[PDB]
Image (cartoon, rainbow, N blue to C red; front, top):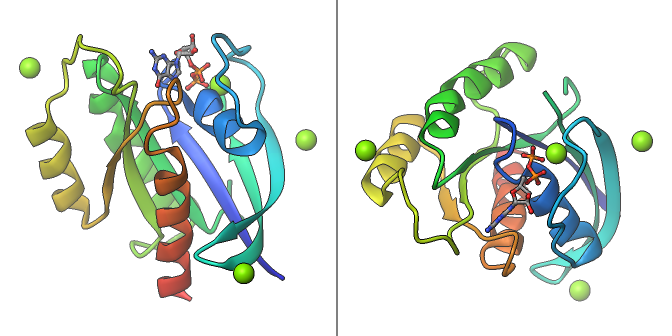
Amino acid sequence: MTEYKLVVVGAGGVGKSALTIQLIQNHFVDEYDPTIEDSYRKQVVIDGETCLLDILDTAGMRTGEGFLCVFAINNSKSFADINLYREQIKRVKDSDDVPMVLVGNKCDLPTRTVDTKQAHELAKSYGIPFIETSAKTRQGVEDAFYTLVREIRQYR
Ligand SMILES: Nc1nc2c(ncn2[C@@H]2O[C@H](COP(=O)(O)OP(=O)(O)O)[C@@H](O)[C@H]2O)c(=O)[nH]1
Ligand SMILES: [Mg+2]
Ligand SMILES: [Mg+2]
Ligand SMILES: [Mg+2]
Ligand SMILES: [Mg+2]
């Protein structure tokens, strides 16, 4: 079956692990050791297609085929840091055309300090999709990962 190597990047505490575990294990982690970096695998169906996802949950690469660049909507600094991660990815892949998706996580929270204009304008600056997620409620989580897969499909 088709295989896709995904990588989740972003500042500490944004929800990289929570997003990954919601996808892989279907549950929300209220805490997850910020030092655990691992790959997590799952056979899934995306748009009817059976495939294998291999997801690298990073902690603060070269074989990654698509990247989620994650910030938290209640963490301005995490948004500022997105550019460092995007550039890291461009360098590690030696390419400007790497599939990626901008993810604004923790959208369940009312304490928003990165607005929807900021996020949408950044995504337009990168020419990539922006997806609002909550690892807590599961809103957007499949959409974020699967959109990335569809970006890899396009790229292939
Ligand atoms: N309210 C809320 N909290 C979240 C969400 N995603 C992650 N968290 C919490 O934010 C903290 C850091 O998440 P974690 O996945 O460890 O972030 P990482 O350092 O990027 O892996 C944890 O306490 C999570 O339970 C979310 O969508 N909403
Ligand atoms: Mg983590
Ligand atoms: Mg491992
Ligand atoms: Mg099918
Ligand atoms: Mg502001």
